[PDB]
Amino acid sequence: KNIADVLDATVARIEQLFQQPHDGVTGVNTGYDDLNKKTAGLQPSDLIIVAARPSMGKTTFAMNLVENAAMLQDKPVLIFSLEMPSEQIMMRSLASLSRVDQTKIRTGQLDDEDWARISGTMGILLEKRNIYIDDSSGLTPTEVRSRARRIAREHGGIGLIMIDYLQLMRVPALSDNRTLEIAEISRSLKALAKELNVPVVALSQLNRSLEQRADKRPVNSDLRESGSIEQDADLIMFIYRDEVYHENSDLKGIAEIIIGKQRNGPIGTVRLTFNGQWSRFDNYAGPQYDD
Amino acid sequence: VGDLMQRLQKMMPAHIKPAFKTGEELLAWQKEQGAIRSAALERENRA
């Protein structure tokens, strides 16, 4: 068996798992091409776990997905903000969508150019009426569920569910045992995804332990210490920014979404551009440099 | 919807008008602005 025959076999095994199995987005449009190719949209009845260390932008990424879902789809998206107040989040989304520096909204002067963009943004959000935010803190799975059901009955189903980190949720009955508590939360969110037949994006923190490693890119194994989240999850995405860990790097303004697990299809990394100023992610323009 | 849109523009000067009338136009601009800036950033740090 010569080199040609054996190399034929090797490229085949790569060729098989490289290509995506879906033609077009079956799930909800993420608003990011490389991610749409890898996931085929966020699938109904899939528990999706967006997990990262602090300062990676896990919350803003998840919020970008909901912002994109609101524009590219008419049915309602539901956001449970356990961390921040409703209005504190929405001001951030205005900056994100309108691409205006967030500091300028808070303190500095807002340009006539800047004012115009947020006016347009707000008009469109008022037109659609897809975004429903719940700032109630320390919610139980039953509360989260019944509230999601209420929105599903009173309007045209549900498009997307968003949980500002999962660890803020709680179950009184199991509150004494933290591992059991998280196990029930993750299970209930999966059950909820099925009933309403909707993707639920549930954020999660990661403990410091991983930062003792040399390669500090999160691995799936870092969720068993949190609890039974990895088992229940159908799609797991980690956010990593080399810039925060290393003073100077080949890539500086670049972030990367690492798919740790996907039932639907392939595992892999997707590189995105990140903006700290207006808190939004963008597609990477690697394909065409052209000098 | 009516009275809330009134107060929206009382904050701004009188001469401003909305840059986008639909969400599709916003995302067209979002990709445009993102594409060019991502290329610009990539160009700068490589250089």
Image (cartoon, coloured by chain):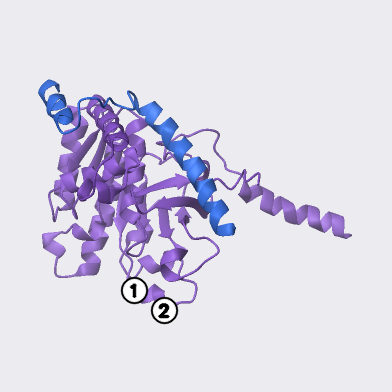
Chain colours: A purple, B blue
Name the mark on residue A208: 1
Disc 1 marks which amino acid? Answer: Arg
Position of residue A132 in the picture relative to residue A172 (left or right):
right
User: Dot 2, crowdedness within 10 Å: few (<14), some or many (≥20)?
Assistant: few
Tell me what residue is drawn at x 30 percent, y 66 percent: A227
Image quadrant of residue A134?
A: top left
Tell me what residue is drawn at x 40 percent, y 73 percent: A210
Residue situated in front as seen by the camera: A110 or A212: A110
Is the residue A170 above or below the residue A62 in the image? below
Name the mark on residue A212: 2
Tell me what residue is drawn at x 48 percent, y 50 percent: A272
Name the mark on residue A6: none
Image quadrant of residue A6?
A: bottom right
For the residues labelled 2 and 1, the Cα–Cα distance comes to: 8 Å
Report in which chain the residue with disc 2 lies. A
User: Badges 2 and 1: C-beta atoms under 8 Å apart?
Assistant: yes
Quadrant housing the C terminus of chain B: bottom right
- Labels in figure, total: 2
Residue situated in front as seen by the camera: A167 or B28: B28
